[PDB]
Image (cartoon, rainbow, N blue to C red; front, side):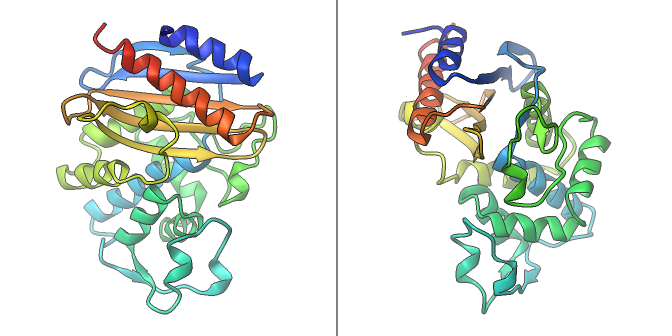
Length: 265
């Protein structure tokens, strides 16, 4: 059962593409292992966690409310919007929008939330404020997923995303209540079944967010651990492959299996 770093390198061969990986201790923030930690990859839909982080920060500051109802129109709908397409009459609350964005990767929910903060530049400013000067969101959904080879728009580094996620979930950046909401949303993710969750034994906790884009781009951010408690952050990205979605999923799942089978080390 291959060691995780061996499996990641194997995944590059199998996919014919770059794979970026890091594993952090949740408590200490220590890097346990990594592969291409400081190379850039398209973040794709994984940005939506950071977006709801920025929204929760505004909520903590009294500039936004979880219950605020947003009405929108047919003309706001973009592709892959399974929740928002059903609420044209009644709208959705900020809370419901983050839930749809994170748990169903609803692209329209994401754009509605971007509007609440003033656009992708404001998400990038929020990130710079909390010390992440690498991760950048430049575009709205779904154009942000274009993944033009070697283009830096809408990218992160595995190390930057992992540390930013840690800061959101466990630091003082958000209130206790907001931190918990953010991890509850990621825990409730319904859209990443074929990725790390496919390798996970019963009794484990995982809170995650997937992403897919053009040029074979695929990835996941996660906080996971045994015994109902997260203990590590895992970040996996790949871009460039011509392999099918199923093939890309299976390589990520296999990286997951490796890190599970060697966890006790």
